[PDB]
Length: 62
Image (cartoon, rainbow, N blue to C red; front, side, top):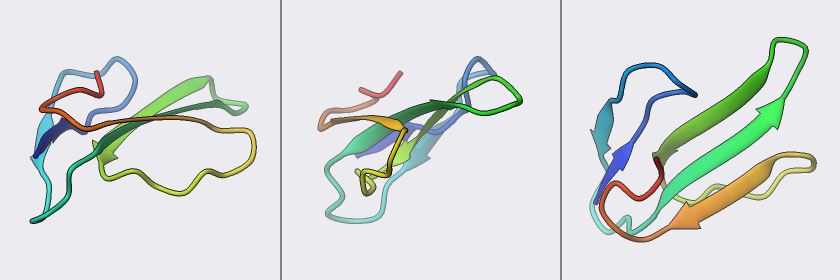
């Protein structure tokens, strides 16, 4: 599995996930700084007030 791992609108970067990892994630939240979009490997645990979208296909978390 290969996922995008860049933040919000910075230039696109990818990451090779560790063996057996099948998902990619896209997290989104706002803080005092702005609207943040985090991307990477896996499907992390759902935490209050943060939007989480998980997908299982190559570079699916744009």
